[PDB]
Image (tube, rainbow over all chains, first blue to last red):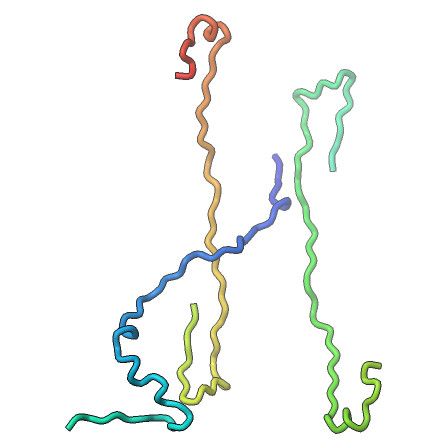
Length: 53
Length: 53
Length: 53
């Protein structure tokens, strides 16, 4: 009987399978444009808006 | 490595042939070899000329 | 797959980072699938017509 398996090597191909993933729906729908760029270096770490009368 | 048969006419039927068996040799990584030096900025300014030498 | 730290200042000095751990999926060979036939030269001459059907 032949024994060949030291002739060859155990190969890990360079490819990845797919992972799982998740949906981002809250981010898209909350308010975006109102707080954009408002907290910056002149502001310190918070800022405020006005409640109605 | 192989072995041979000697017959008058070359008729090899019935007898044993050479199996094929593979061996292999392995080699491994060692430790690092490292030299490390340190010196002050003061010394580079006023002391170490020819640091490459 | 990774995971994340939550710091007030971004100071991660004393903590546990992610570890890289690799898995792999493997696949093999099965048996052969073989279909084999035979027939006599005489049968071919006087009998097997439409051999390709």
